[PDB]
Amino acid sequence: PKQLFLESKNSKMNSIEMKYGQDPAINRAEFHVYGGVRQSKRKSEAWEAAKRITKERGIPNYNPDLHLKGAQMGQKVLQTYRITGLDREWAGGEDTPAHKGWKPGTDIAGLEMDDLNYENNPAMQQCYDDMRRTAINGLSIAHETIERRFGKEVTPETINLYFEMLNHNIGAGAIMMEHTAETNPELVKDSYAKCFTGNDELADALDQRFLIDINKMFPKYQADQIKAEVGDRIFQVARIPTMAVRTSDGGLSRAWVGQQASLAFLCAYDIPAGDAVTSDFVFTIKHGDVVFMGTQLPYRRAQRNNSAGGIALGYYSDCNQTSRTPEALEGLDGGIDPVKVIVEALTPGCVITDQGWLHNYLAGGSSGWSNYIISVYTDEVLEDYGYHGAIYAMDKWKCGVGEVPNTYENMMTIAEEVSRWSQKNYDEYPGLMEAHFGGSQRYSIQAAASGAAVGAMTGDPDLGNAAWHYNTPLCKEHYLRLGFYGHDLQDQQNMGHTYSYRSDQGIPYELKGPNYPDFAMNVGHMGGYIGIIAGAAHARGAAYSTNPIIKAAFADPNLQFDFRYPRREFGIGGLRQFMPAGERDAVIPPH
Amino acid sequence: AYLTEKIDLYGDNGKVLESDIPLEAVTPVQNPAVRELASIFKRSVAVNLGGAQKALSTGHYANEYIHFPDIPNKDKLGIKSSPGGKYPPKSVKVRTMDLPLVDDADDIAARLKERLQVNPDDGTEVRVMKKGNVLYVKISEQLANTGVEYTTALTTTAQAMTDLVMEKYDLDFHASPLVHCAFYGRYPQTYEFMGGNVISLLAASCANEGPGFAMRNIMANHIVAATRKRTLEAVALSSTLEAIGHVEMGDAIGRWRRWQALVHACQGLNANNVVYDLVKEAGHGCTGDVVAATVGRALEDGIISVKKTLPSGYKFYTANDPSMWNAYVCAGLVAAVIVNQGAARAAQGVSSTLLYFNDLIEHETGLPHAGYGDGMGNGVSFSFFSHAIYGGGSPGIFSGNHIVTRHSKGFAIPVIAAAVSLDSGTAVYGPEATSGLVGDIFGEVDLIRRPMEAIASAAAEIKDKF
Amino acid sequence: AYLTEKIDLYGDNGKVLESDIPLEAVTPVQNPAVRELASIFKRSVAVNLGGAQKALSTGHYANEYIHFPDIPNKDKLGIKSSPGGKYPPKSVKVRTMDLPLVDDADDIAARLKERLQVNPDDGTEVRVMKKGNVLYVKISEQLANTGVEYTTALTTTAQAMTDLVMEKYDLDFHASPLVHCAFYGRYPQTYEFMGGNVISLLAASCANEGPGFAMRNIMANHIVAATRKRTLEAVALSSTLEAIGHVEMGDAIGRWRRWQALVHACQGLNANNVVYDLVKEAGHGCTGDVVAATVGRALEDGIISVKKTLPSGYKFYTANDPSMWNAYVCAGLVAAVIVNQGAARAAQGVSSTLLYFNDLIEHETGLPHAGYGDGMGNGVSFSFFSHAIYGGGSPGIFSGNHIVTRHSKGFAIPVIAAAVSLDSGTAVYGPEATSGLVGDIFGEVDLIRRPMEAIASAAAEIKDKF
Amino acid sequence: VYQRQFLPADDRVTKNRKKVVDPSVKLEKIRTLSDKDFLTLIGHRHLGEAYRSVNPPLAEIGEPEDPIRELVPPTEGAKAGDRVCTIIMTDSVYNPPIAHYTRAWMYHNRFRGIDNGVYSGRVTLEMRERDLEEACRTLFETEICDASRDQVRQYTCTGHSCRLDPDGMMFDPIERCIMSGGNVVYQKDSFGNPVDTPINMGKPLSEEELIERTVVYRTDRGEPMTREGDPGAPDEEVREALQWSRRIQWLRMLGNMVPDKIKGM
Ligand SMILES: C[C@@H](OP(=O)(O)O)[C@H](NC(=O)CCCCCCS)C(=O)O
Ligand SMILES: C[C@@H](OP(=O)(O)O)[C@H](NC(=O)CCCCCCS)C(=O)O
Ligand SMILES: O=S(=O)(O)CCS
Ligand SMILES: [Cl-]
Ligand SMILES: [Cl-]
Ligand SMILES: [Cl-]
Ligand SMILES: [Cl-]
Ligand SMILES: [Cl-]
Ligand SMILES: [K+]
Ligand SMILES: [K+]
Ligand SMILES: [K+]
Ligand SMILES: [K+]
Ligand SMILES: [K+]
Ligand SMILES: [K+]
Ligand SMILES: [K+]
Ligand SMILES: [K+]
Ligand SMILES: [K+]
Ligand SMILES: [K+]
Ligand SMILES: [K+]
Ligand SMILES: [K+]
Ligand SMILES: [K+]
Ligand SMILES: [K+]
Ligand SMILES: [K+]
Ligand code: NA
Ligand code: NA
Ligand SMILES: [Xe]
Ligand SMILES: [Xe]
Ligand SMILES: [Xe]
Ligand SMILES: [Xe]
Ligand SMILES: [Xe]
Ligand SMILES: [Xe]
Ligand SMILES: [Xe]
Ligand SMILES: [Xe]
Ligand SMILES: [Xe]
């Protein structure tokens, strides 16, 4: 039974061999014989488009012949990529707002690096936009103020009218005033509002078009856990237009919903224009009873709520919906598969924090640092290493996932074996060593596979992530090289900070994030931690890792991005088959 | 030069507390009680042991409905955790723990004091409250003035609690992040110790609207809760905090120093019993009756005089003492709010009274209202942002640092404290809802709860210096 | 409990300054000189009268190439300003003015001191420097401690300057915004007094990375400029500011207090002459020779011992005193930078020495390096962000508050100060470029320029208290 | 003076690491380069050209009174005020006689006044120009430089992890380094610029020589750092590099929890 990177489980594709058309175990290659960028369909097409652009605007742009010392890019193979594990999927074939239904089990192979660049991939951009345009609030206080101050009864009928009105004004219309401007419905068709509740009788009394159905979206055991936390309360989940956050930031969401929800309360309950109660609605939405995807950031990297930088790792873990899919519930031979949850949750975890945030907010440029991150969700490499650690631990400790005692010693044992297996394959397959040519890719992958195995096997997220940092000596003392110049800042320091309680060192992994100082600057890490946190919770029988409200809030088929199968969605964007929201086609000239 | 003009300080019962006090003796740069008030806000924090214990026990750490779940019934979920169900599911407990913090509050307070104290008898205090659920902490001036910041009581208390709990119960390495979370909440992913269990009366040090605004970032609900709704004591606390804030902003300087000191003395300390006298005279009437009483008192005291009589008979008044006229308008402003919002026993109208008491004053005299535009300006912004969809909230959530109400130079927030003190429970975001712990714990500090008498006694101690 | 262990404090010439000093006597919570240093940073500001005068004169207000243009030759531009050219063009002057601020610096200094003074014998100081172009101001402790913030010297000086200039020259109403701009710059559109002419050694109070980081938001170039490149005095100033910062962060507490105090004593104050002795022994060598000297000194002093000898002959060492071992690694770290960057007289390699002195230490002993990961961690981040396209800059622009170098618990910034002090002028963003005014003005304060002797003398004054 | 042990050396690989980093061990010269070819390869200055300076000579810059500074003699480059120049080398993952972290450890132990960065694909060394030239004689002419696996390249450095070419040479996108008549020659300088005549580096070492002298562990040749069965096994049953790695992790974790926890450990 070969490694998954040499033979995918069901399609039997050889992901590494397909890059070269040569046995990846052979240490031999011919260089300078590919015609440079001519071997790339996307860069060749880009060159021809660039010539037209230069002629039209009068300023040169993309020009591959500018490559240093006459050496065009492409002196070696510009490898293509295969999305990991698409041939092992069997569910999620429903049509989505972004594309017709994917046929589960169909692979996406031959993608070029530029197809998985955040700048060129609308699925990756929409993934982030869906997170930041979301506003979540408890409605108890607004209903309390209406009943106690205003004097009107709140019933399923008034809640339904409130949601019909909020869905009319959140993106397009006006209700109370004469002569008022409105937005073109075509530009905001992705904007809407819903609610969820732990009260099954209330859920059954509402118009289901406005309901996030916990009983439908989740398996029984997970629905029971979430409903027990939500209790007899109503939570609103509103998504403002993607186009609106694209003209500003995610901090607009709570303010925007503050305006529209206040108006829908005024109109659904006939409250006079200017009544003092109005201020309680906006205060409740913006501050009184609110859940944010991201918290504010300090002056150097100043941000209001809902920027990728303020999103706690556990919130990135819980907005992923792989935890409620059949693949994650019975993929490990009829049993729960926490590894499927880790490897999927780390895909937006890596792409959003590294490409969406570190790159598209803190640094930038035309590359999107794409090849660094592509390596974590393609060709079954990290997949093979992760499953290797799980199978090893299940056989050694004779138990299931989440049941290996969470001792420091067991963490070290598993980490040593996964590091060994990662190094064994990079050493025995020159073609794989060349595919993941950057040391950071190889270093992050052995550290992530080790953490995934420890997290999935012990159910302990801090211990799972401790295994990541222990890979620093294991990697360094073997190869005598690690990653890029500033890659091991956090790895070195977290070998000590993981179980430290000093002021800015101690903090559970669920609540760490891109503002934890050690993690604020470098790629190839945060996404891995995000996957580990999600998998550790999954392995110990939990429905989420950090916030049940976030988990329920993203169980929604009306989301533009499919949060259940992110690796697949990023591949669909790679095929140019993902239609994002926010485009301004309705009000611009033809093209 | 010293503000040598003499004033009499009266209590809220309309009886003199101290006579012949130079204005200089009530200023924040001189008055020991006002200075001690700022010192108490800087050095005091509360530790919520009950909250910390609950967070660790159930996994509901921090805020926003966060929950790190531990599943004690894995074998009853109907799932297989082993391929083909070879091994039966076994539960684990990895994110929670039960520590008897509340039961051990007395010993915890002792260990916390030893860690915070720099030298014996340095004035460090730890008091057990709410039968062990809360500790009131006040660090020494020695510790507090080590560096330049005001957050040392907050930072040291959180680390001291975390370290002493890890040591006292000899916890294993797994507990380090969880115990840190029990006290710090989401710090350092958040700048604030968000959802933590170490609380200061001051806001996070990243939240100022400008330099020197720390003493202004205190909600009116906190002030009302700490003074237990005693109207003029809430006005005195709010006005005194705004007075300290204006010194730190650099506005109690040069040709504006007397103007700023008089706002504090006249509106905040019932100087010459003006506030009390105006409320007494017009209490059975409307806002307009306070306008009549304010103009009459300004004339009686020689602060204003008739300047010119227009052909219609309308008289323009002139300010013989412009800074004192402004201060009399500020006193009339808080009196008007007491009469208007006091009659309704409902705070909402405070924003309307702020606007129209000033507008009526100008139309009545031809003299500028409080702040030469800020009184009406904030009446407008504050009215708008307490009755519209755009932002804001009910009166009690505003402060001198809130973008909506920051503008007025110290005479606006005290009227909000007066109105919220008189409210009969007409709001949902009232003092009990937003400031319960603040009022129960910090309200026990005599200086915070009843500053009027403390300021007057301290002013009398140094009256002969000026 | 008091840190009673005795240390000897040595000067930069390797001769003892004070013997038998308890570690407790050099801590920021006890030492009067360290406490006075923080007090000086809080209360001192510089007024750039030359800059203010030039901004008003030419209209080049604030920063970023801003210019409010006044056109004195409107009739020579070839344009018509009247329909059909009925009336010839006439120039106007509406955004600029000429005030002799520098020529009147002496009288302005007297007026500023009187405005800032609370009481005659309060300690307020205003000194005229650079022939009238700059004023050094130090407000009194009375004014500085009125409220809770550290920005009072900045806010009061900007307002006193603006008010006194408006009054002295009896300027018309048009001048108010322009004179305010001459001192405040873009405030309040900016939180900072951006492009203004009132400067503090501290950063704007909105800029901290966390609570208690104010004393850490000071660039290494400022420290080097203030100590005029005297290597160990720059190390002492940087280490002392990091020591105060760590107290304010809450990290000099409980079971971590001794560890934190030893970092300051051993790396920052040449305790027991370790730094000097290591540099003396290995000065003619490489980073590796400092590693050999550090391990040898730790063994000689009984700080470490052989734990186990592996079959190959490699020995694992054990720390008999873990906090002192960490402190000896911190001392060896600054010695390593002095030897390595000192040989090249070029600061850039400081980030490489920070990383590899620690990495070599671990490989040599089997013991953890400084900060159990932070020393190598910051060696990595600091190296990366001083040699790549992503951000950062030259060594001198980093500080304890910079996201790249904040992590280490007080032992990283002092090595940057040492390296930049030894630099022969190899950078463009060196101390002269970023900290000229800081070094010329604040460098005149003896305590800032030469803290080592001041700390040792103050420690000897209170050595019998512990 | 305490005698350094440098790192655990229980086998051929770690003993090779110790030789490279120990400054008292002479690195054997395996090739001769003329001064013209040597300077042409570096590409910063040519033979007979005057050294450029970044600041005036040290004696003219008015160094302040500073007793510690007097204990550290400046290098000749520092005394002259030479520009700080960078040289970059890349070691293949396939059995090189020196690898990236060993370069940092060796540089910090053998050369004075350095700046150096370790990356997976390259290693920089930045020193005052004349000092850098002296250091480069060791980097280019001794046993730590196999012409086919340790190459000089200032940018477009990819190749460390790439498959070897048909001649066993490491890939260079700019083709600075080529195989001609069995010899490895630089047909362009370290910056990819033209050279008047190629710089001959001689023959590469044979495969068995490379395996004998390499500092890297490799699973394919049966010499991984962690062998099958080592994970979890007692310290005495694993490589000393793994016993050292486990110890550093235990002490960084316990020490950073409470420093006193590692006392006597
Ligand atoms: C008041 C304040 O809102 P909060 O009271 O803090 O929720 C502020 N908003 C605004 O200023 C809204 C301005 C636009 C709406 C009014 C247009 S007239 C803000 O977002 O910080
Ligand atoms: C370092 C700092 O930049 P400055 O040094 O402050 O210019 C910071 N940037 C970053 O952290 C860039 C992170 C992304 C680049 C590194 C990818 S490994 C920031 O924008 O605040
Ligand atoms: O070469 S560096 O490690 O500085 C950057 C890698 S993108
Ligand atoms: Cl409890
Ligand atoms: Cl806080
Ligand atoms: Cl006046
Ligand atoms: Cl400023
Ligand atoms: Cl600025
Ligand atoms: K070419
Ligand atoms: K539905
Ligand atoms: K709570
Ligand atoms: K636990
Ligand atoms: K007890
Ligand atoms: K003590
Ligand atoms: K103080
Ligand atoms: K607070
Ligand atoms: K009391
Ligand atoms: K001038
Ligand atoms: K003018
Ligand atoms: K004065
Ligand atoms: K400054
Ligand atoms: K200790
Ligand atoms: K062995
Ligand atoms: Na254990
Ligand atoms: Na020659
Ligand atoms: Xe990067
Ligand atoms: Xe390590
Ligand atoms: Xe990852
Ligand atoms: Xe308060
Ligand atoms: Xe008064
Ligand atoms: Xe400084
Ligand atoms: Xe020491
Ligand atoms: Xe070379
Ligand atoms: Xe070996």
Image (tube, coloured by chain):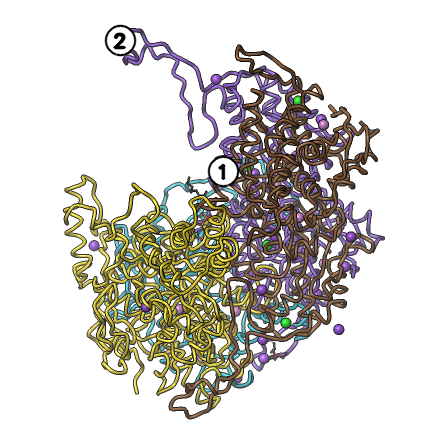
Chain colours: A yellow, B brown, C purple, D cyan
What chain letter is assigned to the residue under label 1?
B
* Residue furthest to the front: B284
Determine which of the numbered discs, if any, sits on residue B381 in the image. 1
Q: Residue at x 64, y 21 (%)?
A: B322
Residue to which mark 2 is pinned: C85
Q: Residue at x 78, y 61 (%)?
A: C1
- Can you give x and y, in whole percent of width and height, for residue A553 in the image? 40, 65
Secondary structure at badge 2 equals helix
Determine which of the numbered discs, if any, sits on residue D169 in the image. none
- Can you give x and y, in whole percent of width and height, for residue A105 in the image? 24, 78
User: For this view, does C245 lie left or right of residue A109?
Assistant: right
Q: Residues within 10 Å of mark 2 (few under 14, many from 20)?
A: few
Q: Residues within 10 Å of mark 1 (few under 14, many from 20)?
A: some
Secondary structure at badge 1 equals helix
Task: In the rendered view, tell whether residue B126 sits above or below residue A208.
Answer: above
Separation of disc 2 and disc 1 at Cα? 47 Å
- Can you give x and y, in whole percent of width and height, for residue B376 in the image? 53, 31
Between residues B113 and D84, which one lies in front from this camera angle? B113
- Can you give x and y, in whole percent of width and height, for residue B155 in the image? 64, 56
Q: Quadrant of ligand 30?
A: top right
Between residues A20 and B264, which one lies in front from this camera angle? B264
Note whether residue D30 is visible. Answer: no
Task: In the rendered view, tell whether residue C420 sits above or below residue A186.
Answer: above
Q: Could you tell me the amino acid type at mark 2?
A: Gly
Task: In the rendered view, tell whether residue D32 sits above or below residue A365.
Answer: below
Q: Could you tell me the amino acid type at mark 1?
A: Ser
What chain letter is assigned to the residue under label 2?
C
Q: Which quadrant of the view contains residue B340?
A: top right
Q: Residue at x 34, y 76 (%)?
A: A325
